[PDB]
Length: 571
Ligand SMILES: [Mg+2]
Image 1: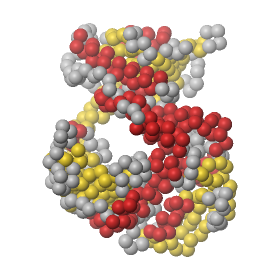
Image 2: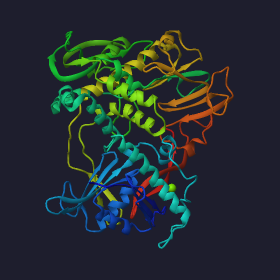
Image 3: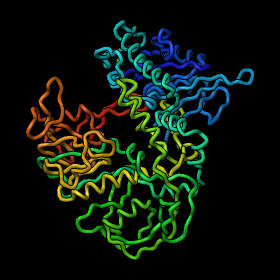
Image 4: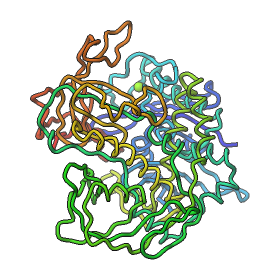
């Protein structure tokens, strides 16, 4: 029986003197078992003996100090097994999921200790988790920048903050495990709950594993959320607008849209209506010109290093090569002018509208009938399922090693690939999601300012007539009027500012209307802008070029990781 602990470290902030000055572990199941010390050597000695599963919140940080220690004490990275070595799962983008430490076997059973990231099961900060789950949290925090030399004695106050931090996580994981959510990720917890509802027998039949090439072709037709800013209102500031958000976007498409399942049938040329294979992805070749008065639809995203959804308005001379779901293709034909269209071939799929209703009915009920902890978990169950279908291909990741200067280094690991769940599903759930947002914005073309996956920003404060019949404060899939603003400024995608009418507070602040309001709250939304930097944004300050050296960023140094301030700039 594998024990489970909730751990944490407290470290120094000096680049030249980076080290762990306090640690702590608590038994997720028995919160009476726990220890707080000031020696990493002492913690690691325990780690090697415990033969259990440990969780750190945001392993990307703690894991650096851990690997640093292992590498200095006879441990080397090893792709799989081999006594006195450790394996890892760090993604190409630097996301840490696991540190497996092996010490050999004994009587044909291996002796080890695996470390995981609790941030993958509960994707929020500790404080937030404390508030939302109704967990006792100590007011304030350690003086993160107080001198702590070798030999430092943890004071009784600091001692309670460490115990509290690890206890908050310990209570959350426990509640989560007592609810049957016993996975490494929240995403996998959803898939388990889903598979538990339709059987691993029906699952396997409904979501077969496609060939490597067949999966790659499907992936060609996958896109993310629709995030677009009207060039017209670009950078210039405006006044008086409204914002509409879809009530649970993804669970809504999954609830009643025609979704794919089963083995695809390959066809040549243009798709012909097939009652049994209602859905399809078509490989087409053409040239196009966005029509006058229509929003761009054909996108290109996630490029080489940095993204920022780019929407083409024309092929401009060159014949384009595209793979589109029938949902995306239908929108393309309306918004653009297509030239010399050549249908090459595609994929047909069986489809149904009832694969997710039971799973969604079950957890939406629990969500509506619960509070705090159980309620946040219900939301996680409902929100993390979509992600499992629109998952990635190769598991190629970063492999650590210790450099001569004492700090960690990383190199690309050998190629490595896993198995898709069912790519066709992720393609169509996002397509319908985009179709929902796009058609609504296009219907309000005259007043449209901005779009971001599940929301639309319009000028004016009056609900458009064409949207009236699909607006609702709580109904699944309906557009909920989320706020009205007196003025705003949009610099770029996901980069805007608004003055929101905030209804008088009868004890607590809410969104108000231009008639019934009390406060005018200023809110900022920006790419990598911290709450510290946001508290310096002003309407004539907010513009491309804005910068400030207050954005902390991790840096591998001997010892482990340290946070340094790096210039954040709105470009
Ligand atoms: Mg603390």
